[PDB]
Each structure stands twice: as C-alpha cells, then as structure tokens.
Amino acid sequence: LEEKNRMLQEDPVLFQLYKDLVVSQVISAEEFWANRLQDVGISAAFLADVRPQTDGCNGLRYNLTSDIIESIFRTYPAVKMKYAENVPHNMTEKEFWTRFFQSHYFHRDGVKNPLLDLTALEDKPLDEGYKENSNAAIIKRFNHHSAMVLAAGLRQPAVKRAKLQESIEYEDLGKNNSVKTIALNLKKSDRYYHGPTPIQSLQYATSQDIINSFQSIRQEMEAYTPKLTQVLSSSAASSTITALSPGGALMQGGTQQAINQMVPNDIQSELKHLYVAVGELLRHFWSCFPVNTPFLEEKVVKMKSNLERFQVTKLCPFQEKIRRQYLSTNLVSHIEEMLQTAYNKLHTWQSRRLMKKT
Amino acid sequence: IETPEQAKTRERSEKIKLEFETYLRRAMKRFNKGVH
C-alpha cells in the first residue's frame, strides 16, 4: 500500500486518474492494478581508481557508497567477514576503513587436462639427481584478486576429447554451409503492377476511327506554326484571375475560427484526462479481444461495465459543464463515437458467440 | 592517508617535545641526586 501510494504520488495525473476510477467506484483497486503490473558487474579497477578524497582543507572525504562496498565484498569476502565481526560493537565503520587504508591490505605496494596440468605435462618426474619475498607476495595477492574477480563474474574423458576436438579442428578444412535462407517466388507478379489502386474505368477507344483521329491530328500538327496572340486573351485572363481571386472556386473555403478561445484550458485539460482514461480502458478491452478463452468474456464484460461507470460519473458531469457554457465544440462527440464503437463491437461479438452456440 | 605533511609535522613536534622533556627529566634527576 505504501509503495503503491508513493508510486501514485510520483504520477499525480495517474493518482488523480486512480482516484477518479476508484473513489467513483468505476473500477476496483484490484482491477486497477491488475493491468498496471539492475545489477552491475565486477570491475577490476574498483581499488586503484577509488582513493580517499584528500580535499585541501584537510578533508578526508571517503565518499562511502553502497556499490563500492558491495564490489569490495564480492571481490574480497574477507572484508565482509571483518565488517560483520566488528561493527557496530567492536569498531565503527569509518575507523575500520581508516584502518584498512593504513594497513598493508590496501597499501600492498585445472578443469581442462591438456594445456593446464603442468605437473603432468612431463612423463619423467624423477628426483633432484638427474625483495624476493615482497615480489612473491605481491604476485600471489594480485593473482588471488584476479581469480576472485573472475569468479565474481559468474556470480572426465568426454571433456578432454571435446577440448582436443576444438583445439585440433581447422576452420579452413571443414564445412562452410551458411545457407540459412529461404528463397521466395510469388505466383502472380502482376498484383503489384496495379496494386491497392482500385479498378478504374480505363475505357478503350473505338474501331479504326481511332487511327483516323490519330492520322488527322498527325497531319494537323505536322504543319504547325507557333502563335502568340492566340495563346491567351484578357477575357480568359479575367476568368483566370477571378478563379484565382480570393473567395474563388480555386480558393477553397477561407478564414476559420479560433478554436483555442472557444474552449477553456481547464476543459481542455479535463478532456485530455478523459481521453487518456478512455484510451487505456479501450486499450485493455482490445488487448482482451479477440476472446479466444472463456475467461476473456468476463474480463470484457467487466471492461464494458467500467466504461459505462466512467462515462456516467465523468462525461455526464463533463457534458453538463460544457453545456452550461454552451460550448459549440463537439468534443464529447469523439468520446461518444469511441464508446459506441466499443459497445457495438462487444455486442456484435456476443451475437456471434450466441450464433455459434446455436 | 589524509594530509601527510600535517602528520609529519605532528611527528616532528612530538619528537622535539620528547627530546626536550627527556633531557629535562635527566637534568632533574641529576639535580636531585646531587642534592642528596
């Protein structure tokens, strides 16, 4: 409940929507939330990069972060044991970190058989008859840290034979099939040539009289001379101007009205809220559709009931609010269209279900 | 691990104060033994 309340507070419009849907008894919180409902890998640089921030005013900013401590614990389980065995009783956390900095711990400055069993690589293991310490310690602890990081990354003759097969096989002298494709060859390619364009009454011309007309025009334009006066006339020019004149046939319509001032911004915002609510309700309705299981029938019936309740409890007050101002905008018409479309869809599907059963 | 120069100065001050107080202690012991 507390988490849900916080999440609703994070989205006040949804919180307002949740209120308008639940308090108005349109939908239950169970049905409301029925449809409503990061790990970081281990980096090896978490030690060298992370340093005690020595701000000039003698400031030892540790910048203690949970992720850094978790990375330390994953890489060094011993640090987790030290933390669990000391705090909060034996010592404080910051004192433990300071001790870690001062200690030498911070200031430190085979499954596969063939190519791993170095002890077994030789078949003649006879007897011995036929700052070095600092360097060895540094190497050992570096290898330990690397192994710990690699392990934290995750968090038999058959194996030997498989490893040998992987090692010996050459990609050149194998197979190169790579034919994971399916060829396609349609039946009638003429569908696209005249595609979604509907059938047009492309009438053909008459009999050889078409050829006679072609010959007539061919002879007519065979002896052609350019003309200038005949190109245009003032009367034709006047007609063209009138067609192009404001308010003319070519100038379709004209000026329009400022819709913004015709509706208050509060009414516009409430319309947005109702749009989002109805849109989500119908989205869930269409998600349930088509009803392929008997459970979906009850869910869609509940969806329709919720739509009816929301309409009655919000749009009708919204309709009255608009009507009191006598707004000429039919914003409610869009909502009515959507609601009636959904209701008719459900009624038609119920009719189909009744017909199938009978 | 924080302001190493301050720590070194503190160590030097402790060293010089320790030398001063130890030689004062030796002088005091000499004084009282001579009095005895």
Image: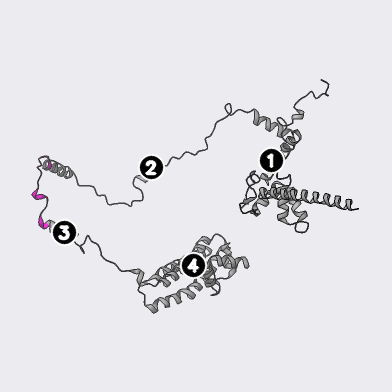
In the image, are marks 2 and 3 on the same chain? yes
Query: Of the residues under marks 2 and 1, which one precedes in the sequence?
Result: 1
Q: Nearer the viewer, mark 4 or mark 1?
A: 1
Query: In the rendered image, which quarter contains the N terminus of chain A?
Result: bottom right
In the rendered image, the vertical position of residue A135 relative to residue A263, given as above or below:
above
The mark nearer the N terminus, 2 or 4, is 2
Q: Which residue is mark 3?
A: A241
Is A54 included in the stretch rendered in magenta?
no
> Start and end of the magenta stretch?
A221-235
* Residue closer to the observer: A216 or B29: B29
CA distance for labels 4 and 1:
55 Å
The residue under label 2 is: A189
First-in-chain label (4 vs 3):
3
Amino acid bearing label 1: Ser
Q: Position of residue A216 (x, y in %)?
A: 12, 43
Name which residue type carries label 4: Ala
Task: Measure how far apart labels 2 and 3 are at the Cα level.
Answer: 48 Å
Do discs 2 and 1 belong to a common subunit? yes
Query: Which of label 2 and label 4 is nearer to you?
Result: 4
Q: What residue lies at 68% left-to-right and 52% top-to-bottom?
A: A69
Pinpoint residue A289: horizontal percent, then vertical percent: 51, 61
